[PDB]
Length: 176
Ligand SMILES: [Mg+2]
Image 1: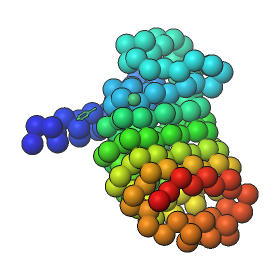
Image 2: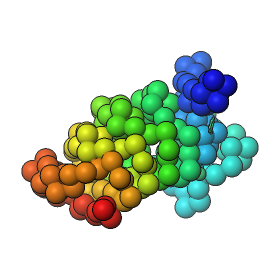
Image 3: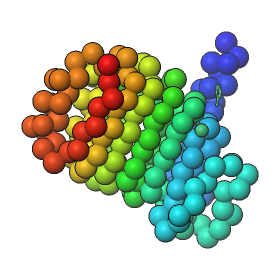
Image 4: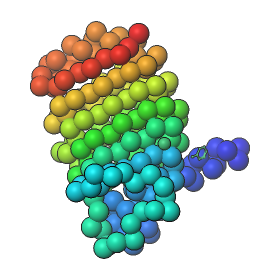
């Protein structure tokens, strides 16, 4: 379908673009065009409107935080994350296209494993226990907030999983 193609092309990585402007800028473009926001290291204010992204020095701005709320990001769009070195915070909220496979894909990016400190996943209806468990690879994670994830059926086992795998993790659960 047309809408399927559209979502796919919103997400697809253009490697030429990564070459031309660097990973952080290319990923900023992906996020904003898909209804997400980013905040750079060194900045208080967030980037929220695509057309207002900095023109700036080549590859100077580095993503520190991502807030994807009511966003169409999914699956291979996360390949934009591969070259990002400094991402510390990610919120996924009302991301209706995200699945366990998205979280798996994220969890396997070594660059994110090294940097990630805080994650929030809220009202993403497809996400299950499998996808949450994958996040244990984010070995430096200090805070994880899960809310309104109807696919997460075994919260107690998640609590115990993280207790051993990430003993210093602050886990906040707003789950039925
Ligand atoms: Mg948004």
